[PDB]
Image (tube, rainbow, N blue to C red; front, side):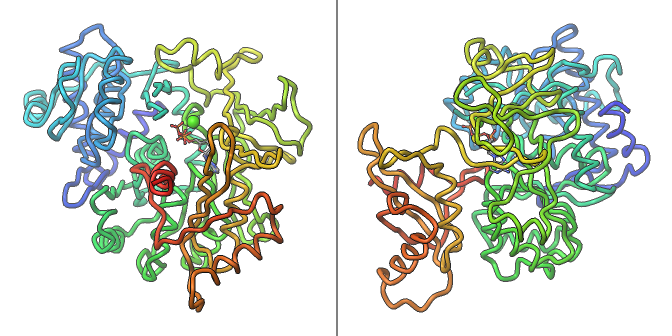
Length: 500
Ligand SMILES: Nc1ncnc2c1ncn2[C@@H]1O[C@H](COP(=O)(O)OP(=O)(O)OP(=O)(O)O)[C@@H](O)[C@H]1O
Ligand SMILES: [Ca+2]
């Protein structure tokens, strides 16, 4: 029943099954409950009637998960902080959030923070000192109490409650057709809510989380060696991450014979990427999902079949979970007729209760409609018979020749051209106005003897897809597209190197 109870069920039924593994470090469900219980018991003894959020610092160590559960068992929401988050932002989070404690298995490198730091051996000592102890079942986070708080770079703390997470997880477990005892890949740092899509569905279904870290990602040979040993069955990642893995010829069914489900969220999933996955993994089901962190990971989802790939050049993002609903709003706070583009607004139990301590910010994006919470995504899109389509971020809309064009739509067409394997549009601005567009593309196999031949071929094909003023003036070619630590296109890095 209760989220924690459905997880703990596996501690009793399959105590020795691995719950989380990172390189050679692993922990069973039995161990997870034990240490988590010990930590919650300790938290409860150190902060008797306190329920302040607790920071959990690290990368992919099993302790990250132990600490998450320990925090909620004592009634505290946790704040995931990845090692890749700049110290400056960590310092802010420590102050924006009334957190009084930070937990980390590894050494904390961020300059003195206004919180009690429990790390390294000090964390080990609580697992030992409180070994065998159990917390008051009644202290566990429940109802509309915060379960976790994830900050959205920008930096505001999105508060996700117990009800919010239960609403997402139940839907994920049912509609993503997960089973039990499956191996789940974890690619996203815990500071990115995409990780929630694999963490909880895995735990409630007695699965095994197989973590891949930053260093491994940097060393392809290590990365691919890990996947080969993983036996991963449920793959949760950003589209960019899968695309990079796709650059390796051995990334196929042969490497992951028991692959059964691909779950994507966070960015546009190119029709081309899905096609390649079906070819490489004819036994796997591909799911595209959409949603902002402010709406608890994702609210829409759709099975990307051959038929879907056939009728939608640009893949839809899915049907809204049944306990929530969508609204497409145009120019004014008026609702748009189905088919018309407008700003995507989400309403239902998946919507966050708001940004932590940010009144003005919450008032601008969060609203109440018929008694329930609503959230303006800032995303442009439309619906057709319950199916939601994503056009792009309003903030990314470029204007040239008095014409407005979603940046993402231009990338869609560039990506669709022959000889293009990966591509990003970098707008070059001359002040407040757009000067011209620069296309960064990863060339596919070709026989062009000189660069201009390739650029000419792409511009000609692109001329059949876009108005001339939408076609990028300059092209740059490179073997790969950079990703941020979260696994998304590093647009800022690209703008930087093109500017210079
Ligand atoms: N399936 C999808 N297809 C296209 N875009 C998607 C999809 N899923 C999510 N997105 C995009 O990602 C956004 C949500 O990402 P997230 O909440 O993790 O932070 P962010 O907006 O990307 O960056 P920041 O933290 O600065 O706000 C959505 O608003 C949408 O623009
Ligand atoms: Ca956002």
